[PDB]
Length: 442
Image (cartoon, rainbow, N blue to C red; front, side, top):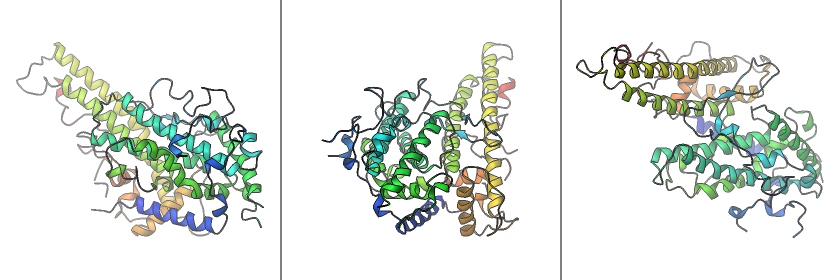
């Protein structure tokens, strides 16, 4: 049901992590353990990871231009409430769409986009040189998230508890996105990302020959993405050192429990949740921030037209400002609602195909994440018992149910239910607000 069922996504992610660990052990997980200090950067043959600088990078550009955040978020939109998510610049079919989070679009990966593949591989230490640039991007992106979140929301120095958790989640989303970029699972197709993926395909080609000194990855260049298994194993071997680079900045926050409980101990499991589901949960959080802000504008502009003995005549300025505030509310909620209808339809299509595709049968796929989505939903349906057409006992059968099980929608005010029925008053996309239906009419 959309409207107590246990939340199990995180325990499912733990299962995916164990499977990746054991499968890497059968191959060359041990030969892929890297150390940034053992790499060579800009041909320099000469401590704490939190002291990594711009010199420990193979960005092929001059000083002050080879930073990881170089030229990112020129309009300061990354963490501004109300920024509209836009579709990927996929020009081939456009039948398939996934909305890009503003945090992801302005991610600090510029050093990785402008790598010199010779400097990374010519010395035969591409395993260690790649980790240095990944750790540099992870640390600078985490630092930029903390500062720009406080800037774009004008957060005073005593940060509230809910804003600290929101910042901690954003850093976990960035850690998961970076793992999907390295492994080739990331869904954003763009000019800069195509160039970035091209560098990794050359680097990991040399890596396959670097550790080849039997071959545990025969035919891995035939996989899609190229070197799929070798890149999954490299991530398993070094994912914790990547999160350690992000912990250098998270320790400056005071909250240490809740979603911030990985700041000083442990490694989060977000990188094993399919990216299409992570972005949906992030879409719902930022929709609720926009909705709550627009709702406050409606409470103040229409405050006078609420009581039968108010101060709001049907032609005066208080009624006019209230009707104009209702019009702006309906327009913003409607355009966000159009995005949700495409998101929830794709969710349901993948969920239905998961419980139907047998061992030897398949629907064809086509999407970059089809296999990862079907496998995740199959293991979810196996635990919950929802394996036939007709079972409506699990909330995970709809996107709205997934949000209410795993999402963070406490900031939605009065309009909190992401499903219509089971029409309703507390529906998030209700065009006439039940509390202000009469206020907009004066």
